[PDB]
Length: 320
Image (cartoon, rainbow, N blue to C red; front, side, top):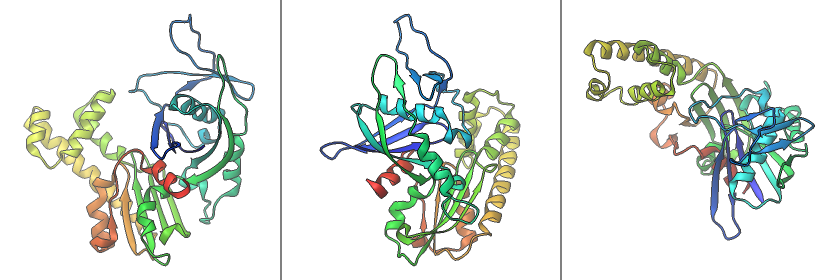
């Protein structure tokens, strides 16, 4: 069994192909604590032992998900989170070969060449043996690693000429990933990552202009205000105050301009691309500005955003 794994900063997504031919997907949390979870036998608990330390699944509010850092990708918890996903996936316990991920700037070095040191370190991490109290665990055999953003653009790359060059612009909640890839994924010419640029720049500007609480509830409100920014009636309906509307609107417009400018300034470091692709949760917010700035023709511009499984699905298409 070959399992494709998107072990990102907020959760674990799996994709694999069953005996017949059906493609299955699964998502699991990244919430684990460094201690034994006790049960009086009333609720289900997962107690693990990895290198020496013990760990347990720590179920928390789907509203308090913690975003992890780069170092997390080489930790014990990373390994436990993957094994836990396999255990709750539905797959039968067994030996499995896997493909996991490393962030763009971790997979590649500043010379745009694959950083062998990091990749090998990622692979060695899954060699640690794991046990589960009260049951058995999967056994990870072969481990391959893929960079994060690029697989999401494979479907498009597949139809490009190897001499063609695709500029993949991936704007997320808190980060920006840009990479120039040769047609059919026949090579990489340049990679660029910014960890302080994302949709949050606009979201925080909105939360601040409304004095919204820190609750995730205000996050949804802010998300909605951004989504429906051009529909003044939607807003009047939401924010009850013509004055608040004007205030939130210009704070939002100001934040978006700064967003567009910062993204374009980074794009100014790339050159030689023939096709452009914009993806990520913030794709809608910069779509127009990049199209105008790159002056690329419509048949050479792509917006393949579909779902949260885009990445792992792309990984699947590449190495199924």
